[PDB]
Length: 229
Length: 240
Image (spheres, rainbow over the protein chains, first blue to last red):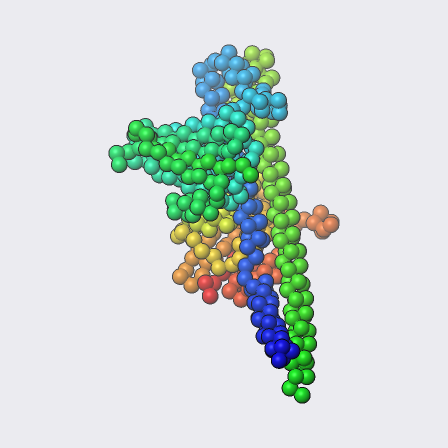
């Protein structure tokens, strides 16, 4: 009767349970720790930023050495003095209060995204593709995990850069726009005469990520709006 | 009796599930401790590299400011002389430095490209001659991210510390791929002057927690060679 029923049901239920626990032991012993791997990816994004910062610094310093060289070869002490007072004393001083003044890549306060854009600016500079950065306001935060935000931005700039190679007098423009409601990443490039799948995957698994495209008179636009939580 | 059995069964399945549930919980704790070690290890490593790079950058900007004397004295002859003798050669060393970094393009394992570039920048800014050779693209290495990363780091950090004392240091790095496996090699010039024992005790600990990683994978073969005055560290990682 209902004792036997319930007792037989019990030995069944406990066997199911024993099965699912045996599966959880097996997953924890043998499948990859997704979380530990995500910590490792996030670490790689930091060290890429650090590497790309030091490369930009080397590129920048070489240009300062070129400029000084030129002044010296022109025998132009007035210019050298003016340039040193205006560019190299401030660089040495390195005052925080001069942060209110800086309005370009210097206002991107997410270290990992700043390094990533620094790399794309350097890649473009190698291939004689001019690249403007418009970040009028400081951008301290973006409501997307670092891994997806990183892949998204890099693919959009990879598109722009590949598209700029088959062209005379190209240009790429980049902007970060903060409202009260969202952060918006825009990339425009000049067009010729007319991967990106993993990017659509990301926008479709996020309700706050709106991916937009525009063809506007001999230049292509990619836009990502990210809404605050 | 028949029924005394099921009552006996439920008892013994409940006991089994208890033990399993203790196992799951002990493994969740082991995984938790591991996530923690990985986060603090890698967050400390970022701090030490970030602070080293800043120092390098500080030295660079200091050098620019040694021109200040010459400018205030309105002395262009002393500037031209000082610059063309002390400062301007940096820009050649920096252009060569940028060229050597193009040696890493064939590394298509994003997992470790940042790690390797960072050791190369570090060696370059310590004025240790370094080259990297990857004759064919390498897009797949058959060892976990974390252990590959720890192995590479130890070997490159060993080659770099051992190179700071020496008069003419060289480090050579390579990734080669057969169709069988991938091999990672770091050659560095052995020192002539051997350190006093007391100026070395508080690499050898790190070489053993490298053997740790090599022993606990059958498909990774570690080799340590001395050959014509070079320490060679080879790690072969088979696609078995």
